[PDB]
Image: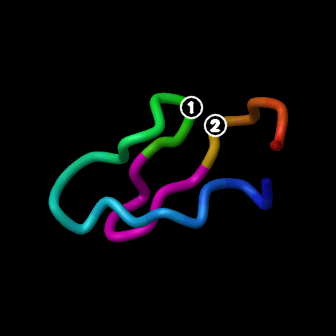
Amino acid sequence: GGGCGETCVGGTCNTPGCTCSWPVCTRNGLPVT
């Protein structure tokens, strides 16, 4: 996807491929689905 459009406002992301760049998740250089 376009990185990780999920947020980690609570503290962490749900997808382990995503990293928390609080409050937004990102994807740590991994293949982008």
Kind of residue sitting beneath label 1: Gly
Give the labeled residue for mark 2. Answer: 28
Sooner in the amino-acid sequence: mark 2 or mark 1: 1
Secondary structure of the residue carrying tag 1 is: loop
Horizontal side of 12 relative to 18 (left or right) equals: left
Q: Is residue 8 above or below residue 13?
A: below
> Quadrant location of residue 3?
bottom right
Task: Check if residue 18 falls in the magenta segment.
Answer: no
Residue plotted at (18% across, 53% down): 11
Q: Main secondary structure of the magenta part?
A: strand
Q: Nearer the viewer, residue 14 or 25?
A: 14
Task: Check if residue 21 falls in the magenta segment.
Answer: yes
Horizontal side of 23 relative to 11 (left or right) equals: right
Give the labeled residue for mark 1. Answer: 17
Residue plotted at (44% across, 67% down): 24
Residue plotted at (82% across, 42% down): 32
Assess disc 1: are there few (<14), some (14-19) or many (≥20) residues with their C-alpha within 10 Å of its C-alpha.
some
Mark whose residue sits in front, 2 or 1:
1
Q: Nearer the viewer, residue 32 or 19?
A: 32
Q: Which residues are magenta?
A: 20-26
> Quadrant location of residue 9?
bottom left
Residues under numbered marks 2 and 1 in contact, where contact means CB atoms less than 8 Å apart? yes
Q: Is residue 26 above or below residue 32?
A: below
Assess disc 2: are there few (<14), some (14-19) or many (≥20) residues with their C-alpha within 10 Å of its C-alpha.
some
Q: Which mark is residue 27?
A: none
